[PDB]
Length: 331
Image: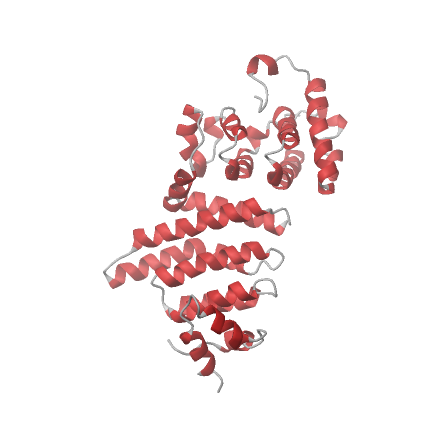
């Protein structure tokens, strides 16, 4: 029942004493980032000292929604002690480790090497832990951090967990509460998990390989589609282009799929992602059919000195097929 204090200390603290300590933390977050200020009326108001969750189903839904929004917002700062104190308040007062334990695990997950992660493990109720996170059961029992490699392998073998990681990341993006560590945690997990799923699904039998490919695209296709059109977050777009490049260069995918990706890419790309996207469009054409759609072609020639940029990309990449399909598609 505490992120900071051992049980002997915590049982004797009054809410007045908890609040006064955690509120200093929240007030420090407000000075770093004014987006914290609206929760001053809500989760961190003085009256919250006496709010008992149990005492109202629609209220609890609205509090669950405010808690989840705060967790997304605070996730970028979990290495600071003010952030840990603000979370502690929600844990002590609103018991969010029991009623919001899925959002809370996802918020802390990219910080799996900091001590607060293990402290959080030691107070999670194991039977309220969602199914896609229960690979953490050994690490709760041993009070040691899971290594990145254990998270990669579980994400690779459990669509559940990859999907929870994607959903949390996309929801932060939609609420403009993302941060660099989050984008990078997602992109690297998804890159290696997709690479691991490709290797597990590799077949010498055409029928098996085609089905595997359809299974894989059903798991990860929508997530990659949403991230490729997140125009306010170039970092998530560029991360998704890295995943799509692995699918093109390693994945053995039919030309309707690669074409689908090509068009989703040029639909979402902006002046901030033009070069990395063009590198991606190139690897999608090299691994495809010789002539490309009009969607793609009408967008690709709006790229400032396109021929100059392709000669550059040719330093490290196979560029013939995209210029060829650009050529062959003006008719």
